[PDB]
Amino acid sequence: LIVNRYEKLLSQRPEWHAPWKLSRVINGHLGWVRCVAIDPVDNEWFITGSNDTTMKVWDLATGKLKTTLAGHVMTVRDVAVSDRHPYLFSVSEDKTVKCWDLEKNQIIRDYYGHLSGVRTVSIHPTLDLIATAGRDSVIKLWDMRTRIPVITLVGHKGPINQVQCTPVDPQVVSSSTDATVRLWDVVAGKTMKVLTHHKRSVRATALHPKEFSVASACTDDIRSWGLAEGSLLTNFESEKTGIINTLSINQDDVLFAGGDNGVLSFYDYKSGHKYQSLATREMVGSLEGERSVLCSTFDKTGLRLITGEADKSIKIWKQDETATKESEPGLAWNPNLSAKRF
Amino acid sequence: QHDMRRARSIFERALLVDSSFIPLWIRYIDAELKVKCINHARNLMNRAISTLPRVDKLWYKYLIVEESLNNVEIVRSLYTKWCSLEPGVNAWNSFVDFEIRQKNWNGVREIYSKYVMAHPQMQTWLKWVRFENRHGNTEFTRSVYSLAIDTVANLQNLQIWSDMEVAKLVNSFAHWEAAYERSSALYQIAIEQLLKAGLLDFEKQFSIEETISYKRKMEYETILSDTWWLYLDLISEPKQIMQTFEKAIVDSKNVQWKRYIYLWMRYICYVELESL
Amino acid sequence: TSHRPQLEARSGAKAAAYTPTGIEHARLLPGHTTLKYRKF
Amino acid sequence: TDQIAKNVKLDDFIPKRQSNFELSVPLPTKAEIQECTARTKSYIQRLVNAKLANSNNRASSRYVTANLLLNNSHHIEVVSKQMDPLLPRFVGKKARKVVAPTENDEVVPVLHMDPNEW
Amino acid sequence: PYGKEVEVLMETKNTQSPQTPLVEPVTERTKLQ
Amino acid sequence: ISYDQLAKLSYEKTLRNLATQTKVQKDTKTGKITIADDDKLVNKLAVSLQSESKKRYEARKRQMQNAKESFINDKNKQFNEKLSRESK
Amino acid sequence: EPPPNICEQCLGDEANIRMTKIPQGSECKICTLPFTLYHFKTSKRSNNIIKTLICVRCATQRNICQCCMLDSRWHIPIQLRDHLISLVNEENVMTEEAKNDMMKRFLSLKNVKLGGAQITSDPSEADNIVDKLKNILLR
Ligand SMILES: [Zn+2]
Ligand SMILES: [Zn+2]
């Protein structure tokens, strides 16, 4: 019964979050930043793989370069720094998954076996395997010792955009251009739950770091999924937002959503409320098409937010610690009845 | 070449490649219907429904096949499944037209009750009003109108529809009860500005001068947001009118100056009509 | 028209269905056989 | 006559945290993480040992880390022989291209709930 | 260019020699060899 | 218009076509639904779908027949018709 | 790694029978895919060595054993049990055997019990078609 659902939404109220404004612009790369990764322990640095093939390791507190990791020859698409290993797995479209030993800053392992370009890594956080998938519509799991494709994951139709791993089954939460967020059984090699609620290519799935859920993003519909059964939790508002490139989920339930239109949209993850919509300013000589926010991540604490855009820039966004619930209340909580998204 | 298990295998591999391509579905359905095999086609279209529920043409073609097969209870089941999936307005309109051409009037009230519960807009309510108005049971039609006004008076806090659609409903209620006292009463209660304008128009449709004058006055103030308007306002008044005139004058480089002068003149005139 | 763009990729389902031949490659020789672990 | 569209429900369409913003989807416990990762580590260890012991590298024998009841009566000891070390260890293994069937056990719902400028 | 709250950082040169690691190779046993 | 409205209008057209024209058992073990379907209705649907396909076939041949700006072969005059339709 | 289908007639009238597994032994004589091949001897001093000649999926697709190539439930040929099911159900249940190589591989990898395998699979419909056979030999 729909009127009861809308009335029960309008009965509840969202949580306030602090408004985000820009604090630091890093203009280092000679190409577009395609994924940003941050060390899950130290927060001393974050590495941004870019289209000029050179990953650069930037600094959180100062915004400095420290090193440049340039072992690829093609566009570095995804970078995933390990949590319990001193490694740095760097999917490019060289068809190569390279491991970077961060005690050495050298390539040590090269995972061959992909049939086309690769788009994403997903280090399984409590085992020694990585989940690489790309244009060839099949997730290859890789044992990090023997460099063997251990478990192929068959069932996505089109190229696979973003793969996330959880420590408990569904251990591979992947999503492709066939608008399916598949939940994988790593043992059986079968899709336990195929989530077909999206319409176009799901370019973004982000793990909630403090609850067992995954947010997935198509164009103008971002949807939060409970991974215990594969149920929709909240369809976010996301009206006319644009093509969503990447998501990222704060510990404090703030959901970033970078659009190709240059727009940002920070979402209250519990309620599904859109509260802040930035306009990323382009550089002084960019084209208007280079406002797009290609990739993003949070801090481990979440008080920072890193975005790699397509204007060869890296922007850092932080919350307003001086705004209150009555000063900057965000956008209004009014669910829309013309959309069934409520 | 008339071997049907081959052609079925070929359409099924084609659905394995891209299951979303609708003409592939429609041609495989029509393929198994040209060979006069409707049990195969019913397995097929149940697959086409369970695959793609939010595509209209698979539903409507299965409804066509069950129309010309004259299996009415099946079509009951098909639409009562399809309407449970919160579908578009065309789905419910097709189901109402189905249970009109199946002359079963007691079902259509339940159908429109669940269609109220699916898509609340006053155009849906007026579809149900128009159905009951063409099919002649004035107790049931005013029951529908009263339930509509009860849902408007219960969903004020929801901002579920505009006040324009509230005016649509209450004006339909008033112009229906002219065929009279009820409509006037509804408007009175309704008053509880645009809605009020509707009351004026309705009274006009069926003391009248003051409301007509007042109603006429409202657009004027709107328009400004000029001299003629001001004059009208003054006429309507008196202090209020004067104030309005003054405001207009104020509102009114050379051009600007001229406007200001005009405003001043107007103000003076107003004062005269009414020294300090 | 003998040269064409790419419509879709060669899917890895077609490589997962093939039975493997044991061709011990020059790079899949065992090397860096120790995984380093962090502090915690 | 409710046998039509058996796999489509509103319980898929309806968001579950919609009615309740407090609705706890909790993280899996430490014991559940330990159990599932021990099971998947044993399974990945099985597949690594299989894909290393089926190699022709003799040095693949160092990074690797049988009774069979048939129908009613035949308690059977299964004894894998010593193969000849010069012969093909897997003579049934052969290069071949295979088309695997993409079977459909249950019909999966595809749920899209929702001109001149293009 | 973006305001005067925002650091704008034009950086082309690596401010750390590439032979140094990023994650430190931690060892509790101080090897005096 | 759009594919939803166009499916709706084609459904209304086919109900108009019927307007110009005009039990259920199950087993225990198999559970397969045997529906009695009258043979006149079966082949009337079959002849109707073949008549719609042949009607669309002849109208499409009628569109194929018409030839009246600058082209080398048949596919080229189709592409030039497409560019003439883009020119508004 | 499924255990093989070998019926009570191939192994023979012994309780302790020692078979030899070779992983990826040979191509099966239905679909030419490799499989774990089990060869043994019926006695200890048998002169004939008896090996599985089909893979497990080709065995369960026909509900047959791997050595004597007859039915698992009935120990009879495939063609004749399909003929008997055609005599019972008045429906020509035939085993669609492939002839192209890719069709052999394709027809073995799919999860189905083709031919008359589904009837003799569970013992309930097995005894149902058995007392239907008794009804036929009463008529
Ligand atoms: Zn076989
Ligand atoms: Zn046998």
Image (cartoon, coloured by chain):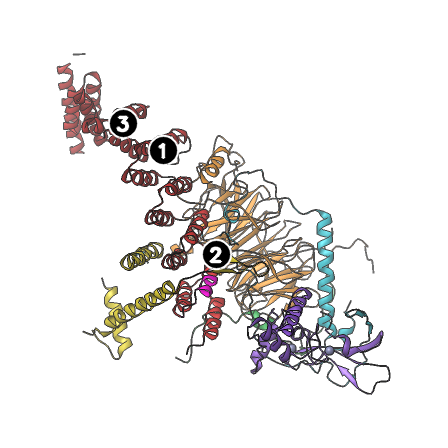
Chain colours: A orange, B red, C green, D cyan, E brown, F yellow, G purple
Circle 2: is it few (<14), some (14-19), or many (20+) Cα within 10 Å?
few
Range drawn in magenta: B35-44
Q: Amino acid at mark 3?
A: Ser
Q: Which mark is residue F24?
A: 2
Find the residue positioned furthest to the top: B276
Separation of residues labelled 3 and 2 (CA atoms): 50 Å
Q: Quadrant of residue B263?
A: top left
Rendered location of residue C16, percent (x, y): 60, 71
Q: In this picture, is G139 found above or below A275?
A: below
Circle 1: is it few (<14), some (14-19), or many (20+) Cα within 10 Å?
many
Q: Amino acid at mark 1?
A: Ala
Rendered location of residue A120, percent (x, y): 56, 60
- Pointer 1 residue: B148
Whether the residue under disc 2 has CB within 8 Å of ligand 1: no
Rendered location of residue A310, percent (x, y): 46, 56
B264 part of magenta stretch: no
On whether disc 2 and disc 1 are found on a single subunit, the reply is: no
Asked if the residue at tag 1 contacts the one at tag 2, i.e. Cβ–Cβ closer than 8 Å, the answer is: no
- Pointer 3 residue: B183
Give the mark, 3 or 1, whose residue is nearer the N terminus.
1
Q: Which mark is residue G70?
A: none
User: Can residue D113 be seen in this snapshot?
Assistant: no
Q: Main secondary structure of the magenta part?
A: helix
Q: Amino acid at mark 2?
A: Val
Q: Chain of mark 3?
A: B
Secondary structure beneath dot 1 equals helix
Tell me which image quadrant ligand 2 sits in.
bottom right
* Quadrant in the picture for the C terminus of chain G: bottom right
Secondary structure beneath dot 3 equals helix
- At x 39%, y 34%, the residue is B159
Secondary structure beneath dot 2 equals strand
Separation of residues labelled 2 and 1 (CA atoms): 40 Å
